[PDB]
Image (cartoon, rainbow over all chains, first blue to last red; front, side, top):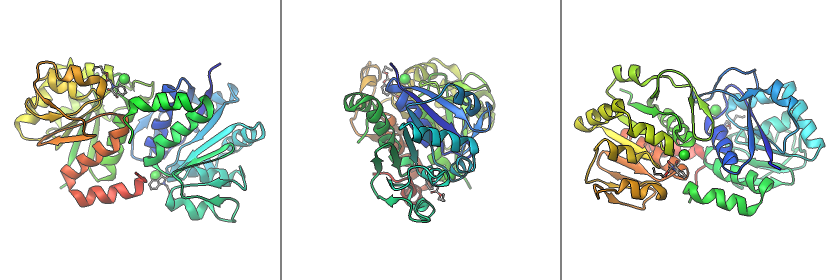
Length: 187
Length: 187
Ligand SMILES: *[C@@]1(=O)C(=O)N([C]C(=O)O[C][C][C][C])C2=[C][C]=[C][C]=C21
Ligand SMILES: *[C@@]1(=O)C(=O)N([C]C(=O)O[C][C][C][C])C2=[C][C]=[C][C]=C21
Ligand SMILES: [Cl-]
Ligand SMILES: [Cl-]
């Protein structure tokens, strides 16, 4: 059976960190739902790219649960995810069921806000380290991608392919990830 | 004065190759117009990401000319660009005025279709080489980014950051490109 991914898309999301994982996961045969935090309407990303979500979060939640929940970064995107009770509920449920949660750039700061994965080794964008580490609830890593059990984090737009391929590997295995990687012309 | 970029967005465009250059160019202070080939409506990209263009191509053309014209790849995107009389006119004008033209993945095959930049050293996605080289009108390169004068080409999603930063360097210089690069967390 096909794996399923929920990508939560908020105003101010970093559009590269949203699109690269969506695209790469689809290349891997994952069924991906791009879910609008605010509803079903188009979302203005951080650099003004406008993306039309597949569904509202409210609706995508009804079709849960998912094999992965993905949190893009972007400062204002991650803040919107951090402030959302709906995101809180989704992440708590995911953690409780031992499902994967993946977050990139400032995205992992939503894990802090929602008290998810405490004690994990994590990375973030360098600029988001201090926010993530407030209280010493995680251990910090400078690895480009950090997978600690079911908490998978990464650093920035430039690590988005690596992040996405790590998700693919976690869900579908090493061999699928390698097959998906080759046509991309990655260094 | 600020440089201006026209990114031509067709149905079936590779969304990573569209979004990474748009975002990176905006980070560089370039004024970017995402122009819908078919009109003003949202565009279904290759992996089903839906992007709302800033304008129709018809309208963006009236605000021309541009310091760069950018052609994303995607097989079906590049075919739509290749078949477009409007794209032909835009590229011929750009070439005649000695403005930069940048194309990635299958995107450079539109240069062939429109008889642009013949004699240039170019690259493409490996799978698009034979189409690009039909007639021996270009010389082929395996470099991740190839800049030959005002024809700038690149290979795939995994070379999109390098492609975008090369555009930035061409328009705004080495130092701006380096400054834009550092926060991205690129290898
Ligand atoms: C990331 O895409 C991203 O999310 N940020 C935001 C950030 O780190 O802000 C720190 C503020 C505390 C949350 C960012 C910054 C720079 C380049 C890329 C990215
Ligand atoms: C590119 O994004 C892309 O454009 N292609 C299409 C391609 O090369 O098709 C060749 C058919 C002749 C035009 C592609 C293919 C695979 C991965 C990435 C990309
Ligand atoms: Cl941001
Ligand atoms: Cl394609």
